[PDB]
Image: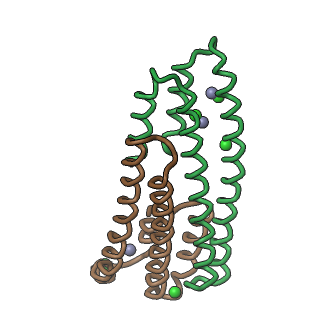
Chain colours: A brown, B green
Amino acid sequence: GDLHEILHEAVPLDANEREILELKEDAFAQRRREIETRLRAANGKLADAIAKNPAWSPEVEAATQEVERAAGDLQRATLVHVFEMRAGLKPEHRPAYDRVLIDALRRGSQ
Amino acid sequence: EAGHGDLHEILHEAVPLDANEREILELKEDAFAQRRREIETRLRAANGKLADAIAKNPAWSPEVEAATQEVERAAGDLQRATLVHVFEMRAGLKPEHRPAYDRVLIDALRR
Ligand SMILES: [Cl-]
Ligand SMILES: [Cl-]
Ligand SMILES: [Cl-]
Ligand SMILES: [Cl-]
Ligand SMILES: [Cl-]
Ligand SMILES: [Zn+2]
Ligand SMILES: [Zn+2]
Ligand SMILES: [Zn+2]
């Protein structure tokens, strides 16, 4: 989320390495849209049901299940993509990248 | 979340402090505040546990995925606890204010 963007900024790189990294982004960008989508949909499902009847209901129950699973999915996809970017780093840059990742996770960033 | 902070103000400002629906309102709030603090503590711990896994071994693993799932679950518990509370508070609000209350709620939900 902002986790994703934070880790991109911990990634030191010249003019060449950046253009290459951006080209490599598209695999994850799409995966992602696919997930920010289901989640944004599950939320609208939630809000729709509440504007209808602001009380718990089978629709609200189902929507919240959907919101949850989707947000987990999104963090998992983010992490997968973050470890792939880690693999493309020179060994000398790995410790700083790990530090940023661990500390962001620890304080609840995604 | 779910516009909670702002919904409570709508409460401070619809049922007067010379009303005593006030007392009941604040007791419900005390209970929710306590449940939230507990769930939040549990989310903080799931976050630490995910961070710990990654520090131990910075790569995707069943251990890291596991932690991820504990985090989603604590987070979902928090949203659910908050929503059911928000509904409870609405049911205790005089019909003359549900309109404005419902606005704030749906707004926030649609974000
Ligand atoms: Cl350069
Ligand atoms: Cl409230
Ligand atoms: Cl208060
Ligand atoms: Cl609290
Ligand atoms: Cl990996
Ligand atoms: Zn990326
Ligand atoms: Zn109050
Ligand atoms: Zn409240």
Kindly identify the residue that appears in the image at 42 percent across and 76 percent down: A12
Say which quarter of the image contains residue B59. bottom right
The x and y percentages for residue B68 are 58, 72
Kindly identify the residue that appears in the image at 35 percent across and 76 percent down: A31
* Relative to A100, residue B3 above or below: above
Comparing A49 with B61, the one in front is A49
* Relative to B85, residue A89 above or below: below
Q: Residue furthest front?
A: A58
Kindly identify the residue that appears in the image at 42 percent across and 71 percent down: A8
* Relative to B96, residue B58 above or below: below
The x and y percentages for residue A28 are 35, 77
The x and y percentages for residue B17 are 62, 15
Comparing B62 with A102, the one in front is B62
* Relative to B58, residue B29 above or below: above
Kindly identify the residue that appears in the image at 53 percent across and 27 percent down: B9
Residue B29 falls left or right of residue A86: right
Residue A49 falls left or right of residue A96: left
